[PDB]
Length: 138
Ligand SMILES: [Cl-]
Ligand SMILES: [Cl-]
Picture 1 (tube, protein in one colour):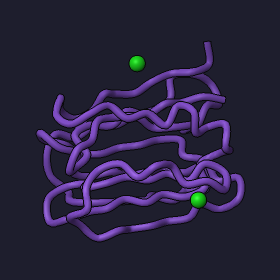
Picture 2: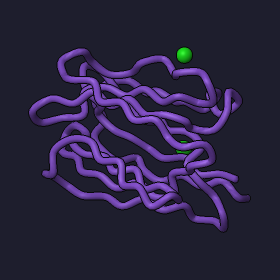
Picture 3: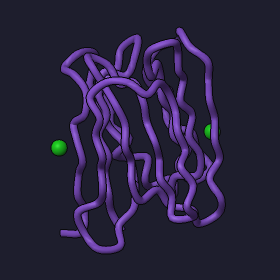
């Protein structure tokens, strides 16, 4: 199998979410991360031309970054406690797309198999992002 999964990173709070179906819309083209003083509050990912359903809460400022045509995420690092605190999306164009506060238990996610990239994300959410998982594929 070429697919692999990294996670789950964070806690057991909130409720499961998965962008598993969203990969049919296209590759990841953009990121939205809502961030407050201490946490990652909310997440949205654009697959092809279509934004995912917003997950997480409302108490924070929206940060939004668009990817270049053909730009793929090849690594994701971050930090968490009871809730997700930081996220860094490392792309194959050498960009490091960083969100949130540099504190907590660190993680460092890389794809298991040859020539795979970030295809979708899952995790847990409520008023914040409780946990995140990364799904790698061709
Ligand atoms: Cl799983
Ligand atoms: Cl949209």
